[PDB]
Image (cartoon, coloured by chain):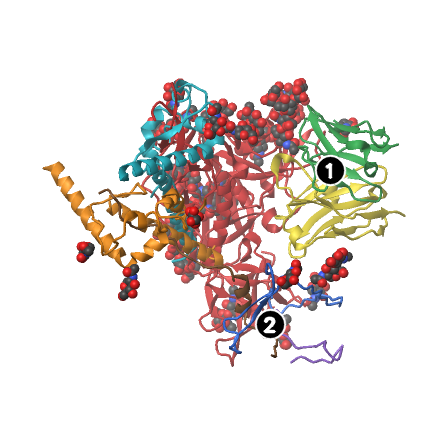
Chain colours: A blue, B purple, C red, D brown, E green, F cyan, G orange, H yellow
Amino acid sequence: LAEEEIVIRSENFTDNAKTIIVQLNESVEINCTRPNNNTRKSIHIGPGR
Amino acid sequence: TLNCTDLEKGEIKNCSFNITTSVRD
Amino acid sequence: EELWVTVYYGVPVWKEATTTLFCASDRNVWATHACVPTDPSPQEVVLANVTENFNMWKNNMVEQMHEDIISLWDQSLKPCVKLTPLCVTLNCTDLEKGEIKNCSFNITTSVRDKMQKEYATFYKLDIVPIDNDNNSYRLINCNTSVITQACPKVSFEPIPIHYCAPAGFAILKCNNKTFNGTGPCTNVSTVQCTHGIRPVVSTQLLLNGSLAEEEIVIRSENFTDNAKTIIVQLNESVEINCTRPNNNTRKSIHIGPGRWFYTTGQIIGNIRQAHCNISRAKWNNTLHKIVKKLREQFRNKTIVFKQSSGGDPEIVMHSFNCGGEFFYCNSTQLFNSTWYGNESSEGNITLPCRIKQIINLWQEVGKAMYAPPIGGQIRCSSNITGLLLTRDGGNNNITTEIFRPGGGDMRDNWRSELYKYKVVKIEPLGVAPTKCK
Amino acid sequence: EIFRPGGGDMRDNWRSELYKYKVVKIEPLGVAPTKCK
Amino acid sequence: EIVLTQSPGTLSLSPGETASLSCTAASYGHMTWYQKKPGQPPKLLIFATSKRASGIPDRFSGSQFGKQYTLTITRMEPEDFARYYCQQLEFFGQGTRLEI
Amino acid sequence: LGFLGAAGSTMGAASMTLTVQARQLLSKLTVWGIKQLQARVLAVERYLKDQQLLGIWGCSGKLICCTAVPWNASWSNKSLDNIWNNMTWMEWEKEISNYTNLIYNLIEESQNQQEKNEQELLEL
Amino acid sequence: LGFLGAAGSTMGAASMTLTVQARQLLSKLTVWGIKQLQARVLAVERYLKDQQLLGIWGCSGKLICCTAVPWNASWSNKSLDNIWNNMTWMEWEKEISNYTNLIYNLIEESQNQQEKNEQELLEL
Amino acid sequence: VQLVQSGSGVKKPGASVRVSCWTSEDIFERTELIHWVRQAPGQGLEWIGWVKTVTGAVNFGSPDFRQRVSLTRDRDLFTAHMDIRGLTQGDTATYFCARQKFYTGGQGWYFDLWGRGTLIVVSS
Ligand SMILES: *[C@@H]1O[C@H](CO)[C@@H](O[C@@H]2O[C@H](CO)[C@@H](O[C@@H]3O[C@H](CO[C@H]4O[C@H](CO)[C@@H](O)[C@H](O)[C@@H]4O)[C@@H](O)[C@H](O[C@H]4O[C@H](CO)[C@@H](O)[C@H](O)[C@@H]4O[C@H]4O[C@H](CO)[C@@H](O)[C@H](O)[C@@H]4O)[C@@H]3O)[C@H](O)[C@H]2NC(C)=O)[C@H](O)[C@H]1NC(C)=O
Ligand SMILES: *[C@@H]1O[C@H](CO)[C@@H](O[C@@H]2O[C@H](CO)[C@@H](O[C@@H]3O[C@H](CO[C@H]4O[C@H](CO)[C@@H](O)[C@H](O)[C@@H]4O)[C@@H](O)[C@H](O[C@H]4O[C@H](CO)[C@@H](O)[C@H](O)[C@@H]4O)[C@@H]3O)[C@H](O)[C@H]2NC(C)=O)[C@H](O)[C@H]1NC(C)=O
Ligand SMILES: *[C@@H]1O[C@H](CO)[C@@H](O[C@@H]2O[C@H](CO)[C@@H](O[C@@H]3O[C@H](CO)[C@@H](O)[C@H](O)[C@@H]3O)[C@H](O)[C@H]2NC(C)=O)[C@H](O)[C@H]1NC(C)=O
Ligand SMILES: *[C@@H]1O[C@H](CO)[C@@H](O[C@@H]2O[C@H](CO)[C@@H](O[C@@H]3O[C@H](CO)[C@@H](O)[C@H](O)[C@@H]3O)[C@H](O)[C@H]2NC(C)=O)[C@H](O)[C@H]1NC(C)=O
Ligand SMILES: *[C@@H]1O[C@H](CO)[C@@H](O[C@@H]2O[C@H](CO)[C@@H](O)[C@H](O)[C@H]2NC(C)=O)[C@H](O)[C@H]1NC(C)=O
Ligand SMILES: *[C@@H]1O[C@H](CO)[C@@H](O[C@@H]2O[C@H](CO)[C@@H](O)[C@H](O)[C@H]2NC(C)=O)[C@H](O)[C@H]1NC(C)=O
Ligand SMILES: *[C@@H]1O[C@H](CO)[C@@H](O[C@@H]2O[C@H](CO)[C@@H](O)[C@H](O)[C@H]2NC(C)=O)[C@H](O)[C@H]1NC(C)=O
Ligand SMILES: *[C@@H]1O[C@H](CO)[C@@H](O[C@@H]2O[C@H](CO)[C@@H](O)[C@H](O)[C@H]2NC(C)=O)[C@H](O)[C@H]1NC(C)=O
Ligand SMILES: *[C@@H]1O[C@H](CO)[C@@H](O[C@@H]2O[C@H](CO)[C@@H](O)[C@H](O)[C@H]2NC(C)=O)[C@H](O)[C@H]1NC(C)=O
Ligand SMILES: *[C@@H]1O[C@H](CO)[C@@H](O[C@@H]2O[C@H](CO)[C@@H](O)[C@H](O)[C@H]2NC(C)=O)[C@H](O)[C@H]1NC(C)=O
Ligand SMILES: *[C@@H]1O[C@H](CO)[C@@H](O[C@@H]2O[C@H](CO)[C@@H](O)[C@H](O)[C@H]2NC(C)=O)[C@H](O)[C@H]1NC(C)=O
Ligand SMILES: *[C@@H]1O[C@H](CO)[C@@H](O[C@@H]2O[C@H](CO)[C@@H](O)[C@H](O)[C@H]2NC(C)=O)[C@H](O)[C@H]1NC(C)=O
Ligand SMILES: *[C@@H]1O[C@H](CO)[C@@H](O)[C@H](O)[C@H]1NC(C)=O
Ligand SMILES: *[C@@H]1O[C@H](CO)[C@@H](O)[C@H](O)[C@H]1NC(C)=O
Ligand SMILES: *[C@@H]1O[C@H](CO)[C@@H](O)[C@H](O)[C@H]1NC(C)=O
Ligand SMILES: *[C@@H]1O[C@H](CO)[C@@H](O)[C@H](O)[C@H]1NC(C)=O
Ligand SMILES: *[C@@H]1O[C@H](CO)[C@@H](O)[C@H](O)[C@H]1NC(C)=O
Ligand SMILES: *[C@@H]1O[C@H](CO)[C@@H](O)[C@H](O)[C@H]1NC(C)=O
Ligand SMILES: *[C@@H]1O[C@H](CO)[C@@H](O)[C@H](O)[C@H]1NC(C)=O
Ligand SMILES: *[C@@H]1O[C@H](CO)[C@@H](O)[C@H](O)[C@H]1NC(C)=O
Ligand SMILES: *[C@@H]1O[C@H](CO)[C@@H](O)[C@H](O)[C@H]1NC(C)=O
Ligand SMILES: *[C@@H]1O[C@H](CO)[C@@H](O)[C@H](O)[C@H]1NC(C)=O
Ligand SMILES: *[C@@H]1O[C@H](CO)[C@@H](O)[C@H](O)[C@H]1NC(C)=O
Ligand SMILES: *[C@@H]1O[C@H](CO)[C@@H](O)[C@H](O)[C@H]1NC(C)=O
Ligand SMILES: *[C@@H]1O[C@H](CO)[C@@H](O)[C@H](O)[C@H]1NC(C)=O
Ligand SMILES: *[C@@H]1O[C@H](CO)[C@@H](O)[C@H](O)[C@H]1NC(C)=O
């Protein structure tokens, strides 16, 4: 995180083809879940494969 | 070739297939 | 007066260290094809008034020998031939109680449009039956692994290799003769390389190692701990003469476009069991001496030798690499006697031996090596220099000690050959007080 | 002004983390005038 | 004849006291200890060389005097009113019970 | 006598092998070939570490040197007879091993001051 | 102070870190393992290039040395106060950077002559 | 992961029972020795034997177990087995699978992990 403010950087803000990188001074929290109780199954596809 | 139908709008499918085993016969 | 700090460089001191050691040595042998020569002769410096602790059970030179044998073995084996195309049903009956079978099979040729039925001779121990029809067989390990046939040009001769220190390092040797494996050694010397050690693959008997100088020396980290290996180093060898008296044909078939596979071809003459001939008097005198020394480690009890109740066949039987062939000899008869405290001292001892071609040294998971067939007849001979023994637990208050062949862990053999050596590093810079500024 | 999520070029993420650093080499030898020969 | 002898067999201590459990080692050697609750598997408390077992929050300690190894329980924490066993390589002791 | 043959000699007597000891510090990607390449690199780096330090100290080019750092009683309060004449170098190095970094740091600082001061006096 | 902490100091003051700077010049074929092997080789070669040159010059073993080469006005016409006391080493190195090869070549030739002449006088 | 323990059946005298225990690859391959013990109700703890994970070599706490009990291990399936023949009422006990990872030599025998245990009952 940035120390004092969100710092926005671009090589050239005028050039619409370039990436603008936004670095925040405070994070935002993201909680990700895949709530499906799965089974791992294995098959062989050759001699030790 | 995989052979299946779906099990969430068809997102997950259970497919059968014909695969040669470690036994070449 | 006053003292000043003085600095000396070239100070004869050292610290314990682990470094990487390299090879040297005095046919395309897997171990020697890309290495360097030894000096015309090693030098020896006796470190008068130097005493140092050695520990054979914590020797990192053993761990390096283990890593090197595996890597060297694999480098040699890797660029050879995959046998996967041969993992098809075999059809056979036997040609010595059904030990050798002549099997036909359906294999795709280098021509992708053609298949050729072909034949190969196999030993019973390398194949298993399919779906109970008493005629169909599969290579025993193909279900889980890739079997690779070793290139016939590779020699497995265990040419001895010397382990040498890099500059800045030295190897110290213990010269006590009757050293028990650890604690201080009061007569030591400095060398640049170890003697050459033969990378012999073995399980119960130690073959072609060094002999003890004065007596049989029996070493164990803890004799009280029945789970540990007891290493017996003899001061006199016992002679073992091994023969596989079957006049064989080497046959080859192709299993793809430049992929040659070698099998046993037509046998000339009849079929006979392989055997190892051990001198009986020598074995009997050796056991008497081993027992006397074992008695010294326990409360003067009667000692009896017995055979193992289990373990992989590679562990239970005594095995070794012969003239490129792999033998599994029935050692039960060598360990079938009771020796007494008041006991003192002509023919041959013969061990029937089985042959296997599919082996897996070091238990590589998912891999196995297929030994090539060897034509003509095979003869080899070895010196028995030691034994890996274990001890039967549950015998407290039984009034006798019971011993069995142990072994199977290759590092226990290397602990014998590397027994006398330790690695140290040289620390040439240091300080002391002086009279002058 | 209209903005959209961009990205997809992994190097643009590394430019953030390595943002503050530069590599230089040390050149320890040099000369100057003195009073003595 | 007897490799490992358990003593005292049974102790009774209120919470806050210190237990002293011990075994005599025939032919000396190192000796380790395990804790058991009814219906449960035992767990390692201390190494035979008196190093504490991982997972033990400094409640157990001990040392050996000649043939006799002594294990102690700090302040009889209630959670530790367990049966204790001695081990010397292949042999186990008879076990010691703790009451209040 | 040979390499490390002086190991059991007293510290004083042992000075007879300082050259000998110094000499043993300096001497296709197959399994052995890779290990050999690493061994050569290690040997070189170790050799140079010692030479750099002797270069910092006013010692390089010599086997024996002295700098302006006094030797005090917290390191050793023994007479030279009970150091140089009644001990081997291994015994000595162990006896004072907790001061290795201290003494070396003192040597560098004193030497830094000696070179800086002598050079300034020559320039001034 | 620390490594390069003298970078903003004047050239004169900066002599206080010459040892410090010198110290930072010296310290299984997996992706990282290969890069590490190359790094060790590079570090050694760089160290030795500097030592060889100091060996050619009558400088090896010292951090500060002088040879018989005069310093003229085409390089610098400043008083020492405006060099040693009013500039940092980076400013200086840039100011005279077009003479690096010239000065170094002059040092080698003068030193070659000094060693050759002194040795002949000793032999004669 | 606690050793997974199967079994807990009831047998008639003369019957055989096979008991096995499982662990994960990471535990199994860091374990040198697998032990079996017995705890008959009210009798205390009796050692049965061991299986070496590398060779399959075995030993026992009694000649009677050596005669009736076959011990083994499986490298691909991270398990161990205790095959008991000739069961009698005197063999009713809780049996346990336990691991020793302590390749510590002379330090002694230690159990890092004991499994849940199984009850084998023999009756008419
Ligand atoms: C403990 O230590 C002992 C002693 O060292 C060791 O026994 C020795 O093992 C080696 C290697 O297996 C044996 O060497 C072989 O000997 C046979 C027989 O040679 C006889 O005739 C020659 C004539 O010149 C005499 O000098 C000799 O003494 C014998 O009387 C040879 O036929 C073998 O040659 C083949 O293998 C070589 C590998 O290096 C090849 O270089 C060579 O070219 C041959 O291979 C080629 O031809 C083959 C034809 O059949 C073909 O199949 C191959 O693919 C290839 O094209 C070889 O020289 C030696 O005789 C043993 N010594 C004794 C006394 O028996 C033990 O093995 C060791 N123990 C353990 C456990 O390791
Ligand atoms: C693996 O194998 C080794 C070797 O067999 C076993 O080592 C034994 O370890 C135990 C416990 O550590 C030792 O027991 C104690 O040793 C002390 C040290 O002995 C030295 O000093 C005495 C001085 O009198 C000498 O006599 C002796 O030879 C040694 O030089 C002793 O001081 C202890 O004595 C206690 O009892 C006496 C009773 O009179 C008291 O006066 C003492 O104060 C003290 O309380 C005691 O003997 C044992 O000696 C070691 N064996 C051997 C042969 O040395 C390992 O234990 C084994 N591993 C496993 C897991 O068992
Ligand atoms: C301590 O270890 C050293 C070895 O490091 C022992 O010295 C060795 O003693 C043997 C005695 O047999 C010497 O052997 C000689 O062999 C030649 C033939 O090669 C023979 O002509 C001689 O008459 C003699 O038998 C060996 O050279 C010598 N080695 C060295 C390096 O000196 C020493 O004896 C050991 N001390 C103790 C107390 O064990
Ligand atoms: C243990 O077994 C070995 C192997 O059989 C015995 O050695 C063998 O002894 C016979 C004589 O009985 C030797 O036979 C001779 O062969 C030559 C071949 O050129 C032939 O010309 C002679 O006329 C004779 O037939 C045989 O060669 C020899 N084996 C070897 C490898 O040399 C040994 O004697 C037995 N020991 C005991 C104690 O029983
Ligand atoms: C995922 O959800 C949990 C539950 O709300 C978040 O944990 C809480 O974070 C706040 C931060 O201010 C704490 O005050 C709470 O005490 C936490 N709750 C608990 C039960 O510990 C968690 O931060 C979320 N993570 C993300 C990335 O969104
Ligand atoms: C293995 O090969 C043999 C032939 O070598 C097969 O046996 C023959 O089977 C035919 C019928 O298909 C009979 O007419 C022949 O008389 C049989 N010959 C002999 C010698 O028995 C056998 O069936 C094959 N087995 C497998 C498993 O493929
Ligand atoms: C070999 O014999 C020596 C004695 O000659 C034993 O040395 C002892 O080692 C222990 C553990 O390091 C020390 O505490 C003792 O003080 C040593 N004894 C003496 C007299 O110094 C050594 O343990 C023996 N090793 C074997 C395998 O038997
Ligand atoms: C294999 O058998 C041969 C034949 O007996 C052994 O060779 C003899 O060894 C003795 C050793 O005392 C010599 O005196 C004889 O002269 C040798 N005989 C011949 C014909 O040379 C050989 O040593 C045996 N090898 C092994 C390992 O058992
Ligand atoms: C395994 O059986 C085959 C089939 O009979 C044998 O190969 C025959 O050998 C004779 C004599 O050399 C030839 O005339 C035939 O043409 C061969 N037939 C085929 C299909 O190749 C083979 O030698 C036997 N192997 C063993 C070890 O006995
Ligand atoms: C192994 O050596 C022992 C000890 O020398 C031999 O013991 C003999 O045992 C018989 C009884 O079965 C006695 O009558 C003999 O007197 C004993 N011999 C001696 C020298 O006392 C034993 O026979 C030897 N084993 C073999 C196979 O020869
Ligand atoms: C292995 O040893 C046996 C003896 O135990 C050999 O068989 C007979 O041995 C006796 C005594 O030495 C001889 O008199 C016989 O002539 C041998 N037998 C036969 C059947 O001819 C056997 O030959 C040895 N085998 C090998 C490969 O060395
Ligand atoms: C087994 O050990 C014997 C020990 O005598 C070895 O025989 C000696 O070998 C050396 C080296 O060739 C000869 O100089 C001796 O003259 C031999 N002595 C005798 C009595 O034969 C024999 O070579 C060893 N065998 C192996 C496999 O190394
Ligand atoms: C992040 O930057 C804004 C703008 O300068 C400021 O108002 C805010 O207090 C800063 N953040 C945190 C998380 O303290
Ligand atoms: C296999 O051999 C057994 C006898 O060992 C016999 O009972 C069985 O019927 C045979 N099976 C076939 C397919 O021939
Ligand atoms: C072997 O070790 C013992 C240790 O007690 C020592 O007394 C003996 O002198 C040593 N033997 C030698 C160097 O030959
Ligand atoms: C081997 O050791 C025993 C026991 O010390 C001795 O009697 C015998 O003479 C020694 N051996 C040889 C082969 O000279
Ligand atoms: C046999 O063991 C006993 C101890 O049980 C001992 O007293 C006796 O001296 C021993 N005999 C011999 C010959 O060492
Ligand atoms: C001693 O000889 C007798 C002879 O009757 C025998 O029974 C006994 O086993 C022998 N050995 C010992 C250690 O007693
Ligand atoms: C195998 O038989 C052939 C027959 O031509 C013979 O020439 C050869 O020498 C024999 N090989 C052996 C080892 O006896
Ligand atoms: C030791 O053996 C004797 C004789 O067989 C027996 O009476 C005694 O009960 C046994 N004691 C132990 C602890 O095993
Ligand atoms: C060993 O001790 C003797 C007797 O005190 C002494 O003369 C000798 O110098 C010592 N050191 C060596 C390396 O011999
Ligand atoms: C020895 O020198 C160190 C470093 O200057 C100092 O800290 C220590 O107190 C001195 N000890 C004595 C006894 O003078
Ligand atoms: C170094 O300090 C430790 C305490 O941390 C002490 O036990 C050891 O003996 C000291 N060693 C030396 C050479 O002073
Ligand atoms: C930076 O500028 C100040 C003020 O002129 C000076 O005292 C100091 O020495 C300069 N350099 C550094 C590295 O501080
Ligand atoms: C400085 O020295 C160089 C090299 O000898 C020479 O070419 C140049 O003219 C000199 N410049 C002055 C101002 O003396
Ligand atoms: C070096 O020469 C170039 C012209 O080629 C000039 O622009 C530059 O300023 C000069 N640099 C120095 C340090 O004299």
The x, y position of residue C115, in whole percent, is 53, 77
Q: Are marks 1 and 2 on the same chain?
A: no
Mark drawn on residue E45: 1
The chain identifier of the residue carrying mark 2 reads B
Asked if one can make out residue D29 in the rendered structure from this viewpoint, the answer is: yes
Q: Residue furthest toward the left?
A: G124
Asked if one can make out residue C300 in the rendered structure from this viewpoint, the answer is: no
Q: Nearer the viewer, residue E20 or F58?
A: F58
- Against G96, residue F76 (above or below) is above
User: Quarter of the image holding residue E52?
Assistant: top right
Mark 2 residue CB less than 8 A from any atom of ligand 6: no
Looking at the rendered structure, the kind of residue marked 1 is Leu
Give the residue displayed 78% in from the left and 53% down from the top.
H6
Residue that numbered label 2 is attached to = B24
The x, y position of residue A44, in whole percent, is 64, 68
Q: CA distance from mark 1 to mark 2?
A: 54 Å
Q: Is residue F85 left or right of residue G112?
A: right
